[PDB]
Length: 48
Length: 48
Length: 48
Length: 281
Picture 1 (cartoon, each protein chain N blue to C red):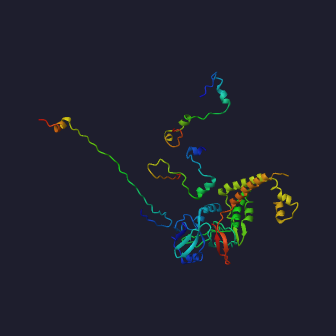
Picture 2: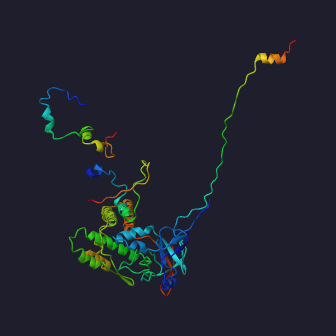
Picture 3: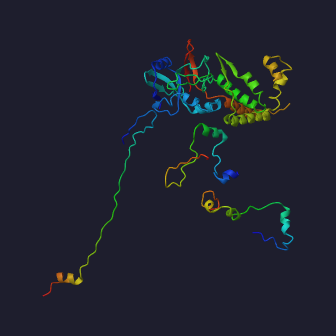
């Protein structure tokens, strides 16, 4: 969502890494770790 | 109902009486048939 | 949290006050899951 | 149903049925409460041979049993009339306590001083009966299970065993029974919490008159209860009414923790002290 009001992300970049927080990997980086057999099972909470 | 009831702690049942009341279903048949106006007037008017 | 998310989401429906009771009386925790076209199913496990 | 005809289903003896013929009026629990049951269910023994086998799980189990009274023992038929709430029934003694006429009786799982053959170990199955104790021995034997579970919280590994043996020989009326080598189990633990919570709230509600009453009484009086308990203002009475009442909510609950179900209330006791007319399931 956030546009961040882009001024210079050359310097704005590690200003995020100053805080040591990461956002949760949000439904595709959490989808790649499912494999072919793993995806079709009931374990996949991302079937929706 | 009959009840084969017995047994040391075998779960017996009581006299389960069942009634039903069956409805009729309608499906009326209708055929048309025509009689010509000429075919009536040569019955009726009866010329010379 | 991670293991039960990795498989077996269900932790408890009862208290610790009733957790001993499921050890005392074997209670039928999991229902008939609605996905039942074959019928009754079994399993067990021995590590080789 | 009330009258429960019982299948024996085992290979009994003449020496079996002679014992129950003199035991007519004993207390037998049944789980299913049919008119026709078998002796696998009839009797209490079938659950006291469990593998964990502590007082914590046997006491909480048999409060789902339904008690019956032994009648008409001839041959292979056991008439067990399920008692109704509030009629007078006589009960033959199953455990050596004289029951002391006028008091409430309860249900004690099993003697658990060893494994007593309740009738005779028939085909390696005996029919063991509950103890019916007069609710003072019931509450005390349930007290000490939590006394020595609170003890094992703050002891290392031996002052439990040096103080359980202090407290396990329960010298009651006609009986010196034994605590069953107290196993720390979670049914105690869920209720030992609420006891410790109930002790906490009484400290909150103790509004410095209920507190200082003994400590003001020792200055004036010299009583046996007052001296043994030495080692062991405001014009708001309407608020003291509500604090004492809320204190009475707790002590009617924390007693109810270690007390049992009220059961057979003695009408009369025979001079034989064996058959006891009792009301009030």
